[PDB]
Image (cartoon, coloured by chain):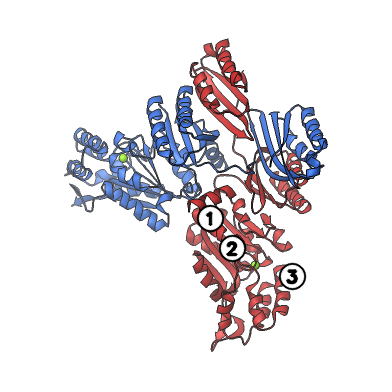
Chain colours: A blue, B red
Amino acid sequence: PKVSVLITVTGVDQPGVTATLFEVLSRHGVELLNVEQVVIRHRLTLGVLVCCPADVADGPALRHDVEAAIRKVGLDVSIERSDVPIIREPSTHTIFVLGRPITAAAFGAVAREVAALGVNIDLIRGVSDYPVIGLELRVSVPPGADGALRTALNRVSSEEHVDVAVEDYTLERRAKRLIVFDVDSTLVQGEVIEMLAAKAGAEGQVAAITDAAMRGELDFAQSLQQRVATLAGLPATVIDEVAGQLELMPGARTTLRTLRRLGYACGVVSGGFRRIIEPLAEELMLDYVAANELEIVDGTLTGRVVGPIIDRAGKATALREFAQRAGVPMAQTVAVGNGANDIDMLAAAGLGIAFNAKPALREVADASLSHPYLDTVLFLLGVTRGEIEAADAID
Amino acid sequence: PKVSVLITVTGVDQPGVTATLFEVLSRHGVELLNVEQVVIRHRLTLGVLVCCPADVADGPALRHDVEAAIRKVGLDVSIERSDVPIIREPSTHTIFVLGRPITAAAFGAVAREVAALGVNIDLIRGVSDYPVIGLELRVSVPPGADGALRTALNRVSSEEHVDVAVEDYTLERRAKRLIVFDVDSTLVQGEVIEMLAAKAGAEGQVAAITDAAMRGELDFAQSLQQRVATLAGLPATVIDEVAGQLELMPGARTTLRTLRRLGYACGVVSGGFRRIIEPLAEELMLDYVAANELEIVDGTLTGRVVGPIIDRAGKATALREFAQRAGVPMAQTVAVGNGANDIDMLAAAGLGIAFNAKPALREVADASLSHPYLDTVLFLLGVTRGEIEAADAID
Ligand SMILES: [Mg+2]
Ligand SMILES: [Mg+2]
């Protein structure tokens, strides 16, 4: 076959259209170069790029056979000489838009910012209807423009009340294989240290300092010392008590379970306390835990921690350690956190996700999530709600 | 917003259409439930499912605003009350069709067999234009019909001279993370044992037995013994000589390199010889080697191997060992081989790929590849040629 022909079928979807076209094409010397077919809301598009004999293409028979067969059953067809890209290039990036709701104005603002920077939209699809509306756009970004893109979509995100994430869509960068979660107000509801403090009747003081520290207004280590000192004199039994009171973030189990299906190494990195966390890590079958450790004398807390202290730099160090042991390059790691002491860890990771985060963190994170559902992380990792439900139904 | 409306835009693709529609929708109380957009060969389809106030939907203004805006620039739009699936379900399987060429008759036969078994085609796209034409169909298979489907497509594949593979498209099953290759006539061109035999002037005898063994006509262990005996009296220097003569299969480096990008554990399992293979495994930075071992006395081959012998069952055992060490469940493993002694290994693996294989193997493999390009394996693993070239250009 010495000449290229492009055949494009559109119209209202009907069964048997696909088979019919290639059966027709088989009466002409047709060999296939590319086929693309989708149906959206009962609208068929079928594009077929072929090679056929010059003799066949320069004759009305191929045309008449195709036009007759397709028009008969009620669709439209176009036929033209090509001689035209065979296969489209991969998208460079993907954009996730999550919201509850996603207004038309929000999405319209995303599409406008995209167009402004010369970014072509290659595909749009929904990735979730629950617990949040989620939409994916795969895009092609002009080289060097993707900084400008992230800045623009960040402005759009704050103004229009949706989450917007722009991620690299290349082969390696999207083979993410390792994830770490902060514990307090990320994997687990609330702040453990405040739960401990309440037992000393110091919930007020400690909560104040915690929120100061999580906004980046206080050095993490000094804030840890001031807060843990509050616990001086509590019996160590308080540790088990609080451990048994802990509630997982909504969507946490689904998140971990789905990540296990995908072969992720999973771990936690916390400035909190190991005796409280390790019990839970075991229950969640995690692969790695880094945390601080309470000092205990004669079955009583002293109000100090045992060095060395996992601080902001310590969390990045822990992630790096974990990924080295697991044999996972940093570019294929994910970190999820909510607070300013997570800043270094999020920056070290391939993908840093700020989850219901203080401004300090959301300001430097690759992506931010604002809804109280930890499983929206999965959407950022290329999973759809449909795929989660299917896998869970298969059990 | 208390009522659902579906808006469907089709026609010749133009810039700014997407932004325009949602800007229009924003003048009505519209919140988004699902957006699907593709462009194929300059044909746009944009389907938008929304919720809006009952008051707005029961009035001509929304309609007129949308119809005017879209028809003006030269596309078509439909608007209708929904009240309709929000997000489509995931496909159950994916079908790969590879050929050189892929005739219209071949693909037509695939589409017909698919339709016959009540299988719906959800998507078609090209995955490669080189070294082979490759097409992907994502499908939804009626429960219990996928055995019948594989049988039908196997008949089609032999008759029409294309490779056809049907794979499960679920979340876990497609997070493949570990792969093993047979060496001889899979990763490496030709048969090492025949190269060794030629040094003894026994290439003829050994080749005969090798091809008998690879077709499953001979017990592998006895055939190994008869063939290695042929080497009795060769100096062990022959091992290095043959090791330096080895040529990788076309596409081997691309295959391994791409699998490394994706975070695969990679290994080889062979009935061949460790002193010949380990040198190469090191060069290819593989994670695991299992092989047999030549007996050497006083720097001379004795013509025997040192037990235990990696036989047909041994290869499955090796794969299982490798996956256990790597922490990879069998369902997420891949095995590639060409011969009958690979039968147990292919059956144990999540995905068993027969590569230019003897009938005995191709008969029980999940998928078969008939072209002399090892990188066509990558297509079966969900990678496109475009993505390989992009990653390689990024270096
Ligand atoms: Mg926290
Ligand atoms: Mg072999």
Residue at the spot x=68%, y=37% of the render?
Answer: A47
> What is the x, y in percent for residue A63?
79, 34
Instruction: Specify few, some or many for label 3: CA neighbours under 10 Å numbering under 14, 14-19, or 20 or more.
Output: some
Q: Amino acid at mark 2?
A: Phe
Residue A90: tell me if it is visible: yes
Separation of residues labelled 1 and 2 (CA atoms): 15 Å
User: Is A94 rendered above or below residue B9?
Assistant: below
Separation of residues labelled 1 and 3 (CA atoms): 36 Å
> Which disc is residue A247 wearing?
none
Q: Is residue B104 left or right of residue B192?
A: right
Q: Determine contact: label 3, label 2, CB under 8 Å.
A: no
Q: Which of A167 and A197 lies nearest the eye of the viewer?
A: A167
- Label 1: which secondary element: helix
User: Is A352 rendered above or below residue B75?
Assistant: below
Instruction: Specify few, some or many for label 2: CA neighbours under 10 Å numbering under 14, 14-19, or 20 or more.
Output: many
The residue identified by callout 2 is B181
> Which disc is residue B258 wearing?
1
> What is the x, y in percent for residue A322?
37, 54
The residue identified by callout 3 is B217
Residue at the spot x=41%, y=25% of the render?
Answer: A160
Q: Amino acid at mark 1?
A: Thr
Closer to the chain start, of discs 1 and 3, is: 3
